[PDB]
Amino acid sequence: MKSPYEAAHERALMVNRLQKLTRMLRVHPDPKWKQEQQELIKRLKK
């Protein structure tokens, strides 16, 4: 039981941050940055 507003908020938070990491990784692929990206990708997948 989760509100769509709230579920949406969390999704937006992770997507927005995920994009930033994906955007900078393409030009500057870092392992540290990559690790953070996986967490975002995994959460979004759920």
Image (tube, helix red, strand yellow):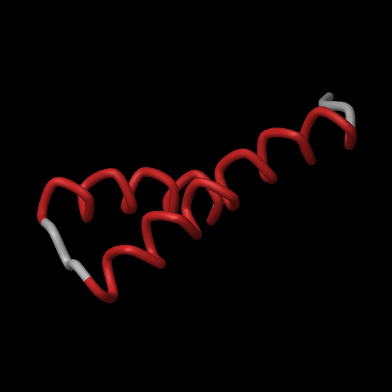
- Front-most of 12 and 42? 12
On the image, the x and y values in percent for residue 13 come to 62, 39
Q: Image height check: is 35 above or below 28?
A: above
Identify the image quadrant of residue 36. top left
Determine the residue positioned at 67% across, 34% down.
Answer: 10
- Horizontal and vertical percent position of residue 46: 57, 49
Where is residue 35 shown, x and y percent of the image? 21, 47
Left or right of 33: which side holds 18?
right
In the rendered image, the vertical position of residue 38 relative to residue 8, given as above or below: below
Farthest residue, direction left: 31
Point 47% across, 53% down: residue:
18
Quadrant of the image containing the N terminus:
top right
Q: Residue at x 17, y 67 (%)?
A: 29
Foreground of the two, 45 or 21: 21
Looking at this rendering, what residue extends furthest in the bottom direction? 26
Q: Image quadrant of residue 25?
A: bottom left
Q: Is residue 36 left or right of residue 46?
A: left
Q: Foreground residue, 46 or 11?
A: 11
How many marks on residues?
0
Which residue is at a point 50% across and 59% down the rendered structure image? 19
